[PDB]
Image 1 (tube, rainbow, N blue to C red):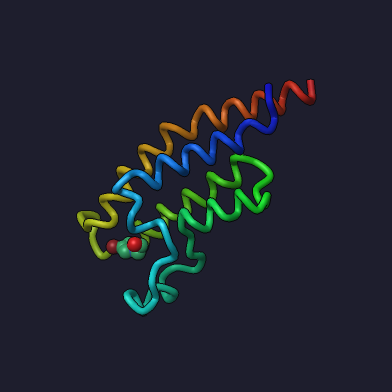
Image 2: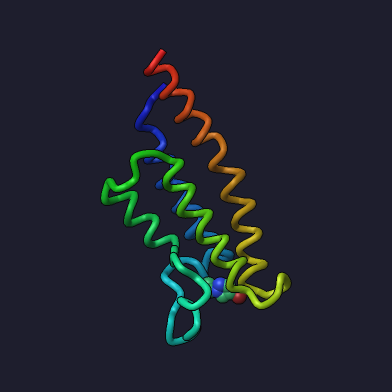
Length: 119
Ligand SMILES: OCCn1cc(Br)cn1
């Protein structure tokens, strides 16, 4: 029932994601010199360094907010891919499966802890 435990759990999960070769295209903001029309397709860029920085700044109140930004990295990749068989999009699908697998208990434990606090 530790209401604050999600934060270090999220830090450790971001460390695992950064060690994963599949996170390479998502570790930093998409390069606009490389993809000049990126902002014509994507309204809200997101990447794992921005997520880690937001977390370390104390700018996430809950793991649900962190989860919304991580899922935005994957939906941006799906929206920008020219094909569902592209290398970067294929890496995003594997990384998203790995993330969802690990974030589920973080979300469950936090929501359980908050319900106990308001019991
Ligand atoms: O690497 C993030 C930029 N991007 C390229 C494709 Br394909 C989808 N998103």
